[PDB]
Length: 19
Length: 128
Ligand code: BEF
Ligand SMILES: [Mg+2]
Image (cartoon, rainbow over all chains, first blue to last red; front, side, top):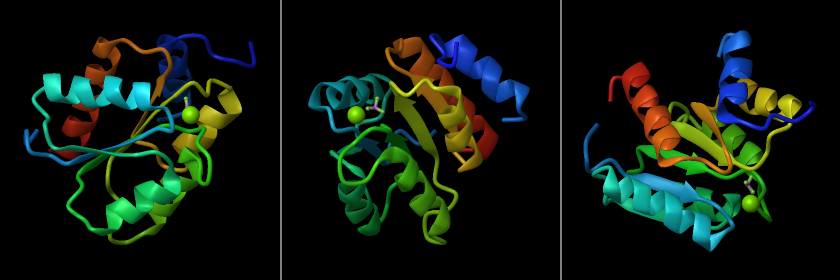
């Protein structure tokens, strides 16, 4: 779980941080 | 966007560059050049005329993060779209790329739909 395994996970991450 | 927009596709892996370059061609973009690492990429960005960069992270000589930082630091290239397309999925690093000013972030393996979706998103944000 230190790793992302999907595009959605990356999108959600970047979104959650104002990107 | 202008179907004559000049793309630079940067990846150490020949096969992946074929993937990206072909997708661009299929989307209407036939003005596409390639670099195998960051040093190569910057040499090529100097001759100018490029409008969009798609870059890998892990490459010899200069990686895609140092390349992103150099492009953003250069007043001649500082607003050029740099889309990361990489196997690198550790959160602290995706964060690093985005803080360094990446225009987007696509993880490998990707679908053609994803690449298209991320491209059209950049075009709109920047009015291309
Ligand atoms: F080697 Be790349 F960062 F997927
Ligand atoms: Mg690589």
